[PDB]
Amino acid sequence: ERDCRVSSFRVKENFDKARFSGTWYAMAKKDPEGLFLQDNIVAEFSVDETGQMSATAKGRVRLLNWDVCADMVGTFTDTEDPAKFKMKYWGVASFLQKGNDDHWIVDTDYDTYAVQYSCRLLNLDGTCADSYSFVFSRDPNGLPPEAQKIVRQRQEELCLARQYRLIVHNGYC
Ligand SMILES: CCCCCCCC/C=C/CCCCCCCC(=O)O
Ligand SMILES: [Cl-]
Ligand SMILES: [Cl-]
Ligand SMILES: [Cl-]
Ligand SMILES: [Cl-]
Ligand SMILES: [Cl-]
């Protein structure tokens, strides 16, 4: 039986903030409870001179049967693992969803694909009770087959492979 304990999940060895910087298009998402980012999700990652990673995102978001284009902001606090962060986030608009989630770079090759994961709440057996995950691509037209195959493996390793939906980019925002 597969190990689905969050503590067991491998993440990106020697994660490199600088190489990860720039534009990432969300191709797929596994939603948490009370999902927020809906579609047209585009992220912009940056790293400052002190070495701190941060990001912005734009996308159609769920407010209520009410969705809207929103700009989000995230700042990442380092942990002992170079691929595991604490992400403080908020909307440019006061009323938008704000919070602090774990933010793991599960895998990336920096120039093609990235797999992100967050467990918001653990089960008592160490599995995740409430998770989300994004698959990003540098190219909004999607991953090449080699990357697609690696990503599928990573999705399976997170015990999430059956639970993603595709994210469309159709110029809405
Ligand atoms: C995984 C975060 C999304 C992409 C990284 C960019 C981070 C910078 C923008 C702030 C993120 C705010 C959105 C956090 C809610 C995610 C959960 C959800 O969409 O349902
Ligand atoms: Cl940068
Ligand atoms: Cl930090
Ligand atoms: Cl555990
Ligand atoms: Cl595969
Ligand atoms: Cl395949």
Image (cartoon, helix red, strand yellow):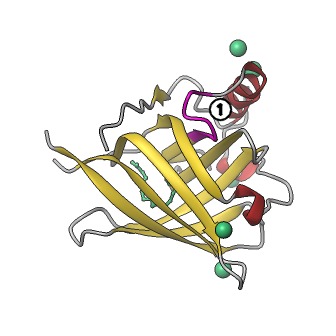
Within the magenta stretch, is there residue 18? no
Instruction: Identify whether 1 is placed above or below 64.
Output: above
| Placement of the C terminus among the 4 image quadrants | top left
Quadrant of the image where one finds ligand 6: top right
Instruction: Identify whether 173 is placed above or below 169.
Output: below
Q: Position of residue 80 (x, y in %)?
A: 77, 73
| Placement of the N terminus among the 4 image quadrants | top right
Give 134 or 5, whichever is nearer the viewer. Answer: 134
Residue named by callout 1: 155
- The three-letter code of the residue at mark 1 reads Gln
Q: Position of residue 165 (x, y in %)?
A: 45, 27
Q: Residue at x 73, y 64 (%)?
A: 17
Within the magenta stretch, is there residue 136? yes
Quadrant position of residue 67: top left
Q: Please tell me whether mark 1 sits on a helix, a strand or a loop.
A: helix
103 horizontally vs 110: left or right: left
Q: Position of residue 136 (x, y in %)?
A: 59, 41
Q: Residue furthest bottom?
A: 50
Q: Position of residue 170 (x, y in %)?
A: 37, 31
Q: Residue furthest right?
A: 14
Instruction: Identify whether 153 is placed above or below 81.
Output: above
Q: Residue at x 65, y 37 (%)?
A: 158
Q: Residue furthest front?
A: 171
147 horizontally vs 166: left or right: right
Q: Is residue 125 visible?
A: no
Q: Which residues are magenta?
A: 135-142
Q: Is residue 73 visible?
A: yes
